[PDB]
View 1 (cartoon, helix red, strand yellow):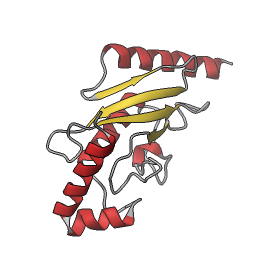
View 2 (spheres, helix red, strand yellow; view 1 turned 135 degrees about the vertical axis):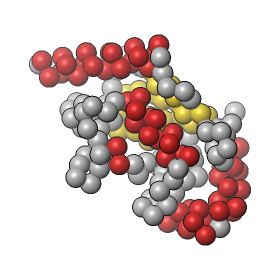
View 3 (cartoon, rainbow, N blue to C red; view 1 turned 90 degrees about the horizontal axis):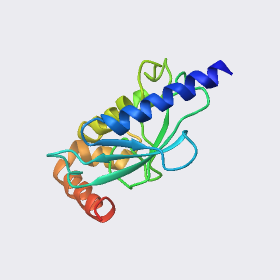
View 4 (cartoon, helix red, strand yellow; view 1 turned 30 degrees about the vertical axis):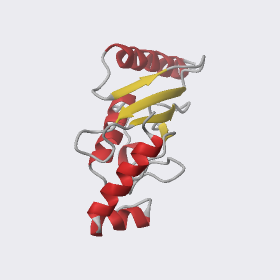
Length: 157
């Protein structure tokens, strides 16, 4: 219908802009005949324990996009207060109001930017991983050692 048509048109424009002018350290692309099962990559940030990490994500675009948020998870394991061992991300822009902050004026590029930012600026007070969040808050040098080790093990070919 015109709904599916407007979503298809929007995804094509988003994927074009991601192919031509992506955000710094952020890429997202089609690798299948599906436009709604996408791959993304975030480079670890300077001066973070994820530096020199290359992080792979799955980006699923639901049928109701852009009125439902993209479903994004890390394929690359990452050691982080707000990302779990299944790669699920606790982030406001990936959930609907009133709890979350997804809105149709956001887009794939901006939510991947928000995930990049979460990697630099964790929310240890709203932890998805209690023990990592406690290490982040009360034993910061141990958190940095462990996060850098995980990066070297998982995020560095």
